Image (cartoon, rainbow, N blue to C red; front, side, top):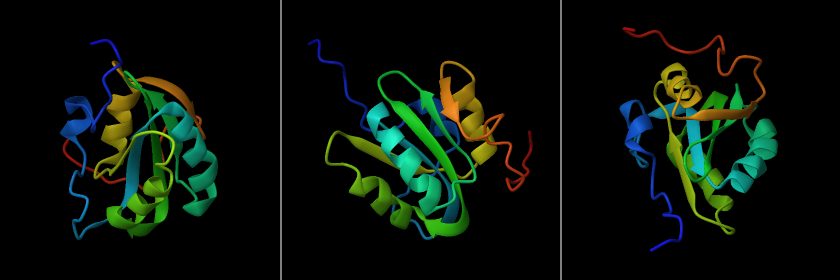
Amino acid sequence: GSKVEDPKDFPSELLSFLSHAVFSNRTLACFAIYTTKEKAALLYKKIMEKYSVTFISRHNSYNHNILFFLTPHRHRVSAINNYAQKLCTFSFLICKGVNKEYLMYSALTRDPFSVIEESLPGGLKEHDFNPESS
């Protein structure tokens, strides 16, 4: 009746370009963590060196923040999932993977998603994404 509603997953807004499958067999190098803000900050200084994040930006959605973060080597969302899971003993946790990095972080920077911080001077813009009808 009043307690802010907790998010059980990503909003249909970013559901236009995501992975979803958690036990799939594809190796993705881009992931989008979605959890309380204090959480994204803990995984920002952590993954920053665990996967040499190709780019990590903390964005603002409606209730919590989405710590976006890429990675060089390849990893199944099941492995990176164990990462965001090891950090789920102080609040809810909704880490997921991403198939289209550029697009994803794109709708995240444009309303209704605001931007908080990021290691890149212009968001992802990493020189290792993939092309696609746009």
